[PDB]
Image (tube, each protein chain N blue to C red):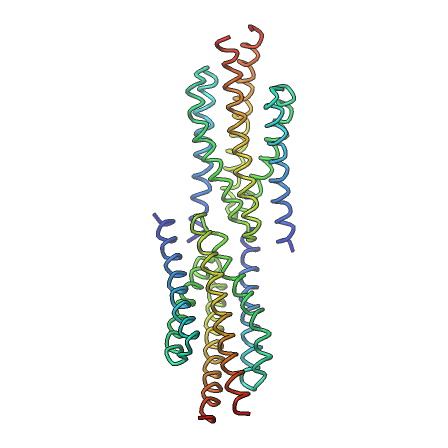
Amino acid sequence: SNAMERHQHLLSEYQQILTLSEQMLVLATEGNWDALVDLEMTYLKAVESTANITISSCSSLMLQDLLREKLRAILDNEIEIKRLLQLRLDRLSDLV
Amino acid sequence: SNAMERHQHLLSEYQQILTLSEQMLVLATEGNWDALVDLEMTYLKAVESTANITISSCSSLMLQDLLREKLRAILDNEIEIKRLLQLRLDRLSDL
Amino acid sequence: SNAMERHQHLLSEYQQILTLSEQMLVLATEGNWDALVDLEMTYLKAVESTANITISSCSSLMLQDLLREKLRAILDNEIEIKRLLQLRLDRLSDLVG
Amino acid sequence: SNAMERHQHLLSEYQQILTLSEQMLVLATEGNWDALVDLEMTYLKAVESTANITISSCSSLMLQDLLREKLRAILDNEIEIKRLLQLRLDRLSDLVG
C-alpha cells in the first residue's frame, strides 16, 4: 500500500500541473501576461517535484546526483529564458 | 539488463533536454528569437519522452492511461501558450 | 516504485499464483472439481496482474496498447474453454448418473 | 536497437500465445478434445517462455532462481491438474457408450 500511496502522489502531481496549465492557458487566452509570471514559479516547481519522483526512485547513487544537477539547470534555464522573453515583451510593449 | 538499460535511457533523456535547454538560452540571450522558436517543439518532445518514463514506472495501467491524457493536455496547453505569445510579440513587433 | 518495491511485488505476485495453483491441485487430487472452478477466476486474475508487470513497464505505447488487448483475449479464451469443458463434464456426468 | 529487439520478442511471444489460445478455443467449441492436450504442452511452453522475460530482467539473482522454481512448480501443477482432468473426463465419456 505504498503502492496505493505512490499512485495518489503521482496522480496528485499531474493533477496539480494540469491545473496550473489550465489557469495559465486562460490567463494567456485573455492576454493577462501579468497574472502569468507568478503562476510560472508554482508550475515549474510542481514539474520539479514530479520529475523528482523518478530520480529519487533510481538505484544509482552517482546518477541521482547528476540528474538533480541537470534538472535544476533545466529549470533555471527555462526561468532565465522566460525572464528574457518577458524582457523583450515589456520592451515592445512600452514602445507601442 | 533493464536496470543498465533504464539508467542509460534516463540519463540520455536528461542530457537531451538540458542540451536543448542550453542551446535555447543562448539564442534567447542573443535575441535570436525565431531561431529559439524552432527548438521548442523538439525540446517539448524530449520532455514528453522523459515524462513517459515516470508514467511507465507506474504499475496501474489504468492510471497510466489517465496520466498519458493529462501529459498530452499539459503539453498542448504549453504549445498553445507559447504561440499566444509569439503572436503578442508580433502584434507589438510590427505595430 | 524503486528496486526493493518492484522485487517485493514481483515475488509477491508469484506467491499468489503458486499458492492458488497448490490449493487447486489439491482439490483436483480428490474430487472437489467444482470447488476448483471458484479458485479459477481468482487464479486467472493473479496471472493477469503478473503478466501486467512486463506490460505496464513497456516503452512503446503502441505495443503496450496491443499487448493489453491480447492478454484480455487470452484470458477470456482460457475462461471460455474451461467453461466448455466444465459444461462437457457437467453434461457427460448427469447423462450417465 | 535493444529496445526494438526486446519489443519484437515480447510481441512475438504474446502473438504465439494468443494464436495457440485461438486454435485451442475453436477446437474446444466444436468438441475435439483430442487435438487439445497436444496444443496444451506447447502453449504452456510459450507461457513459460514469456514469463521468463520478466524473471530474467530482474536484478536480484537470488530472486531469479526462486521465481524460476515457482514458475516451474506452477506449470507442473497446471499440467498435473489438467492431466488429472482428462483422466476424469475420459473416465466418464467411456462408462456411457
